[PDB]
Length: 296
Length: 296
Ligand SMILES: NCCCC[C@@](N)(CC[C@](N)(CCCCN)C(=O)O)C(=O)O
Ligand SMILES: [Mg+2]
Ligand SMILES: [Mg+2]
Ligand SMILES: [Mg+2]
Ligand SMILES: [Mg+2]
Image (cartoon, rainbow over all chains, first blue to last red):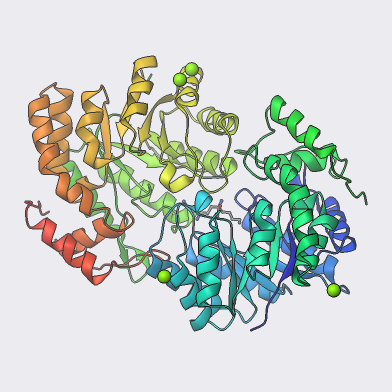
């Protein structure tokens, strides 16, 4: 299978006067490239996919593809939806406009059954010829892609190559790789990046890497080389910021941190997301002081 | 406040060859009117709002409004979204096209904070002058509108008049009405329709009423008349079907039951929803035999 692995960043989407700041977006992607990141994920959960239009979703994918041209860095385009016809349309656009693969979140809100999840992802995978990474985050979607469903999709669909797990369930990570060791398990939960990698995971799709791309890149690379002492050390050092970046719903803390570090010009969200509380703003700022934050 | 209460039905959306069957939809709404229902909810969760287009969402609202003309039956239009700009647009269309109020589900997937939920619903409420019913269903959305947020929105926004609760939490129902007895608490959980009504709830937005509108209407109207003995009797009689209608994710079982009863011509969903397993298909058919299902 064609795969996209390694250290990856779920890119925030900066806004300026309620509009996608397209110049800042490219600048942020360049900073990720220059700090050892291997793939960028435009318009994931962290990129506020819910509140972008279908057009803006497509624009951000285009900026990512163009910015990564001439580099090793891959574009794993966020193209999921809770409507299969929407997810197929987004996947086809990403393929047609040069994305290296797609990240496709499990349908949210409408809670498909395991059979429905299978047909949803089968329709997506058969619509394009680029790699497809499943994305399980039951705390946000209200449903769970079971291990059996993931493994069936991996075995039945040529371009489905793994899953980004954001479920706080290391038991399931063992279940997945013990029964199907050929899939690419990707950490979608920064605090447990190292445990997932040490069990045979092959990458991360990170929130923290927006702020600290060099540290997340180093962690991942040490781990892929089985330098587990060094990878665990970085995972341990990162625990405090990894947790504080979820003191409110992601991406509220990470956008706050990027603003505090001078990496984005305005702390703007699209409703229903908004600025954090004054207390949490201060806690984010306090934890940031422990870490060395790369500029541009 | 202007309010919309009583026995209400979360309408299924019938499909024929992947298209909204508009004639079947109007016929189903008339059947609800003829069986004592006080309001209908087009394109809620049960109506597969997630997989309808914005335009099909607008078409079903028009059919509901047109079918209810010349009757007391109100149209409480499903107009929620996880993007505030989407929810405002849906609310404005519903108002402009004759809906009596809107049902607005809490944002799904992106998990707004309580502050974000407040600003989300304030923006919706300030965009129209018709009643707005909040809708809390954390098992599907991944977030919870707290009692404090619900009460603040009720007190601060003239047209926010209550909440549809589908959270399996009778403690919260006590919390809501003990601190704000002026709001309209609406049951969104058929099995516990009577306990919510007996605590001062003023209506239901029902899945089961799709199949048994006369029984849900009678239950609610008995309760509103403080004939709690007769209301509980119907609630107890309905428990078996109330639970089997969630043996798979709603609306998979209710559409299956409507098809088995001959009320819709095809068992068609839009992916990622699909037909139930053969076992659950048989379980639904078995539970239905206990009940008298009205025709057209
Ligand atoms: N990534 C950009 C697209 C965002 C669209 C949407 N906000 C809503 C998606 C939708 N399926 C639209 C249904 C519209 C008819 N009610 C949903 O709200 O479930 C989402 O998927 O979060
Ligand atoms: Mg097993
Ligand atoms: Mg090496
Ligand atoms: Mg209060
Ligand atoms: Mg309290």
